[PDB]
Amino acid sequence: GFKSGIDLLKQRSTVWKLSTSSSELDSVLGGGLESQSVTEFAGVFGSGKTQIMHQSCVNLQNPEFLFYDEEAVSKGEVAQPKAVYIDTEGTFRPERIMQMAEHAGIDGQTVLDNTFVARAYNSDMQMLFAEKIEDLIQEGNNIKLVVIDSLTSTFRNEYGKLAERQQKLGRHMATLNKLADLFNCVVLVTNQVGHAATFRFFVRKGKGDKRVAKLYDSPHLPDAEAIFRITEKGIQD
Ligand SMILES: Nc1ncnc2c1ncn2[C@@H]1O[C@H](COP(=O)(O)OP(=O)(O)NP(=O)(O)O)[C@@H](O)[C@H]1O
Ligand SMILES: [Mg+2]
Ligand SMILES: [Mg+2]
């Protein structure tokens, strides 16, 4: 039941990464967004949280954007990847998808066909939608990217009794984190500015196109800052 020595390393090797289309961002991420982990992009208004969630669904459809050790992750495991986008804010825009696709050399329609978008209006729908993700897989959908944009808006606006909230939001995370592990996929969640989450960034604005993404929590990477801009191409630099 316990894994030791070489097994630990082999287990860590089944972890693949998704590129953000930003050199700096990827750099700070240790190579890219990690599968089997939950990565949070908390940030200020118009900081780009949503843009990254979009760019992420797009890059998922460009095979050269999935970095993984072939000796530990067969092409068959990352074949025909599909993303699940749980939209809590109603900020999903299929046109931003088309545009990002365009500038990346991807069939925008392919992205839309391989991305499941669930509109959630309350904390119950949110949690439930994240729970059905398994069924989706069970239906033969190779879910490899999950997006909860955002993660804490519903829970906040619904809850003194702030214990029920944490107790519930924690239950959501449990499902999310487990999801990431058993199905070897990347989990992304946003937060406008208490809960688990292996990676945590805080984004902000700079000079126009400019954005400053600060990585302040991860189990094996140092705190660092990546700089990128948002343009009609999506995330870039
Ligand atoms: N087509 C585009 N061309 C250039 N920039 C764009 C385009 N679309 C969006 N942007 C940029 O994206 C910024 C907002 O991105 P967004 O991902 O929605 O931030 P956000 O953190 O999710 N905002 P919020 O949910 O309110 O906290 C804008 O203010 C624009 O500068
Ligand atoms: Mg995990
Ligand atoms: Mg947003």
Image (cartoon, rainbow, N blue to C red):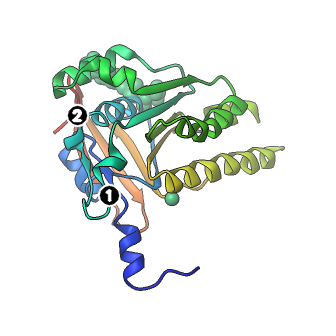
Q: SS at mark 2?
A: strand
- Identify whether 25 is placed above or below 106: below
Image quadrant assignment for residue 129 = top right
Q: Which quarter of the rendered picture does the N terminus lie within?
A: bottom right
Image location of residue 62, percent across then percent down: 24, 35
Residue at image mark 2: 229
Q: Residue at x 61, y 32 (%)?
A: 153
Image location of residue 72, percent across then percent down: 31, 63
The reply to whether residue 194 is visible in this rendering is: no
- Identify whether 27 is placed above or below 151: below
Residue 188 in the figure: left or right of residue 104 = right
Dot 1 amino acid type: Val
The reply to whether residue 61 is visible in this rendering is: yes
Residue 211 in the figure: left or right of residue 137 = left
Dot 2 amino acid type: Arg
Q: Which quarter of the rendered picture does the C terminus lie within?
A: top left
Q: Residues within 10 Å of mark 2 (few under 14, many from 20)?
A: some
Image location of residue 96, percent across then percent down: 32, 18
Q: State which mark lies toward you, 2 or 1.
A: 1
Image quadrant assignment for residue 213 = top left
Residue at image mark 1: 73
Q: Ligand 1 within 8 A of label 2's CB?
A: no
Nearest to N terminus: mark 2 or mark 1: 1
Furthest-top residue in this view: 95
Q: Residues within 10 Å of mark 1 (few under 14, many from 20)?
A: some
Q: Ligand 2 within 8 A of label 1's CB?
A: no
Q: Nearer the viewer, residue 227 or 2?
A: 2
Q: Nearer the viewer, residue 193 or 115?
A: 115
Q: Residue at x 32, y 41 (%)?
A: 79
Image location of residue 39, percent across then percent down: 45, 49
Q: Residue at x 58, y 56 (%)?
A: 196
- Identify whether 45 is placed above or below 8: above
